[PDB]
Length: 54
Length: 62
Image 1 (tube, chains in turn yellow, brown):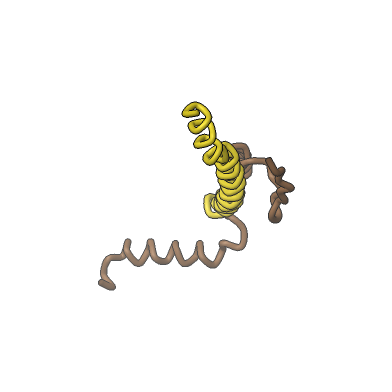
Image 2 (cartoon, rainbow over the protein chains, first blue to last red):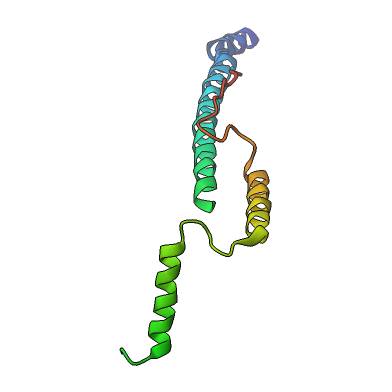
């Protein structure tokens, strides 16, 4: 009986693996977006630094 | 101050250069050779991108 009760207890919290997957996917998309922002910023500043160096 | 004949002499030579600076005077071939060399070096160190405007991205999703 107690073994089954413990199994049922674990059923409630089964969802954490999906929760982890969601957090990972969302924050990975966020990371890619921030990389895009900073990459455009860096390229443009280098681009214009070309002109000032000249 | 109007007495340092070399002071006014240097100022005069500077003025004449200012007037004559339509193209770098007494440049000689060394001027062009250098200009090209170090412009080329700067071009390498910066990059070979489209040297007029903003290059495009076309990123890729995960």
